Amino acid sequence: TGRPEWIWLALGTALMGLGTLYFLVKGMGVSDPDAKKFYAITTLVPAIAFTMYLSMLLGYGLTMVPFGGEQNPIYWARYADWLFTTPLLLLDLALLVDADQGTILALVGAAGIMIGTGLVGALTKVYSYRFVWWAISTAAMLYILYVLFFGFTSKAESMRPEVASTFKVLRNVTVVLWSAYPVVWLIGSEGAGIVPLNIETLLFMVLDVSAKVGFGLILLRSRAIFG
Ligand SMILES: *C/C=C(C)/C=C/C=C(C)/C=C/C1=C(C)CCCC1(C)C
Image (cartoon, rainbow, N blue to C red; front, side, top):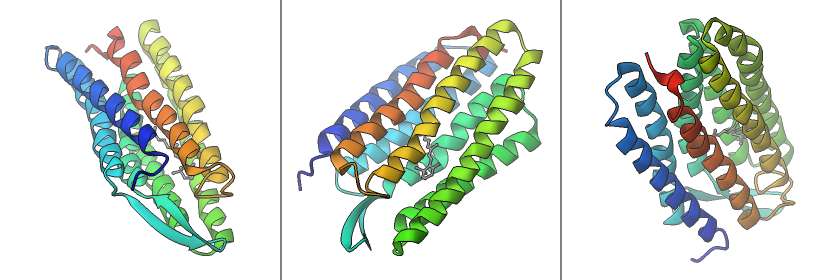
């Protein structure tokens, strides 16, 4: 096939793969129980992303949805990735500030809606309805970010400054990266179709790699992960 976005798919596969192995090797050396906990969640994140970037690289996770008078290329393998990677990143942040079980359940549920309605939207054939679903997904995301900024940050204050300060960074990198996804979807292939797929794939890999491997490096190199 040789689609124009494959080079970006091959770069995301490489970065995710390398990041997985570094975390894995660093994780099986640590003896601390809590550290092990964080290491196992943070290594699984880029491991799932790697398998999906690799599948997309190989021609899977791609479907042609009809709307706007075109046969539009929608990479659904992405939501198969995010359906398990977003709630896992939320768990890393939840365990860090000692969030409650109700909070975690509500954040994971919200994340499920966000990705579910997102895909339903990327698959919808009525152009205007694609944006109705997009709208609900975004509203779910704003709920998650609100909790992370108002809820979590507040409970991270019962932690030590080292733990509170690591959370602020992970919390900030998350608020900045996550807010970007809905905009890329809106002006990209799933939405307006203003930004071409090849460029769109490049934006997503920079966001995906930063949000997982970038997030993992910051978190796993900190002492806040220790029991
Ligand atoms: C490793 C992947 C990460 C951290 C992905 C985060 C993805 C989002 C915050 C995605 C959000 C979306 C919306 C708000 C609405 C439209 C569709 C999505 C799923 C692209």
